[PDB]
Amino acid sequence: GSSGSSGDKEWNEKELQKLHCAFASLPKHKPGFWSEVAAAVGSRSPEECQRKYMENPRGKGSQKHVTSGPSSG
Image (cartoon, rainbow, N blue to C red; front, side, top):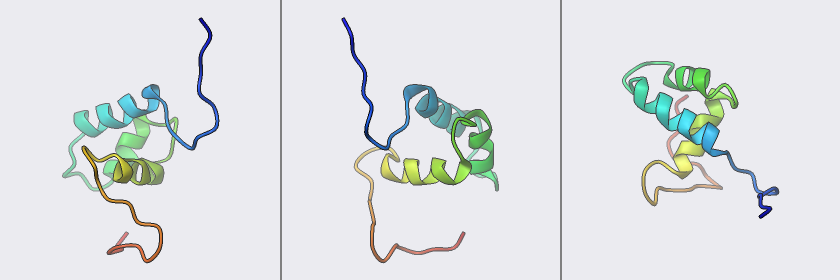
């Protein structure tokens, strides 16, 4: 029947697949990897593709709210 989920800062398959796809299609050895994956993930920003992935890298991962880890940019 009916269904849907609204009200939870999250992406959608279309995005994910785009994030992963690109992330896969495109090399991670590249510089503006985000800018790239962001191309296909246009749906979102390249700076977000990181924040997103960071949460769901592959498995558990690591989250940080206060006093972020090592920052470089």
